[PDB]
Length: 48
Length: 141
Image (cartoon, rainbow over all chains, first blue to last red; front, side, top):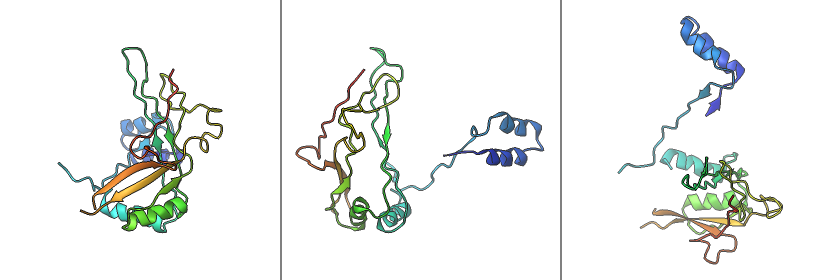
């Protein structure tokens, strides 16, 4: 999990800047707020 | 551990210069009937695994194929923990002065007895019956 930095936050906000409310969400949430969901995908755990 | 990442874990202990996060989370879930807001008192006692250290070289051979390596984890099993009704398994300082070097010498033994049948016994540096029953203490509040 990566706590998004100020620069990272700017990136996300700019990605969704065209849509006002999209950018709003990101921008309103404080920097080091938006966290990165780097969920693991590898298995190993077989299933039962 | 997923096979590609198991081989990567291997590699780390084998060579890969990285520090495996050995978070020894000591979660202490109590109850709420007798009170205890965040009953679960937890603390990840992490041991950054120095790349190919004595412990990690034992782990290299552990994950190579042999199952007879007593991985020396420098005193990292809190034998006295002042846990309260909050979410923290903080050990008592002075009870364990170093409290990272005065916890309790813990050992690890992966028992891959192909028949890999990878088991994992948590031993002690001085395991008497603490390979199956490690006796620490939680100073409860």
